[PDB]
Image (tube, rainbow, N blue to C red; front, top):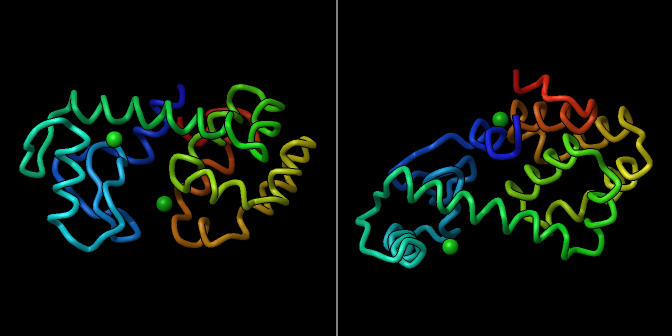
Length: 162
Ligand SMILES: [Cl-]
Ligand SMILES: [Cl-]
């Protein structure tokens, strides 16, 4: 297992524009296109991202390409964030994948606001972090996914994904 397989599991793969759990237009492996209610706006953002007139549909390779970019941007975002980087650097490789997943889902900003959980993770207080992390709108909205990521962070193993 790795970050790519993990997120491919959590996000799935859809070749046609769809709405995510919050109702926003998305395509491929969780690539958010826009927070706007306009499908045309979403189609405009897609064609811009792909480089052609897609008509709301892309191929598997195109989806994988957006995913690679998105994964890359997520890590880089973490390394550029002063609140996030130090946590990330303190972690082992498995736990790091849990941090990347959260950021991919919620944005760096979002994640950087889990102040308390961030500190517990940095101090290696696993169980405590796990409980603090669950006290969030994130967990109440997407509990099954939130449980898998929380367990990854708590245990440093891929068990939730086997
Ligand atoms: Cl893009
Ligand atoms: Cl879920």
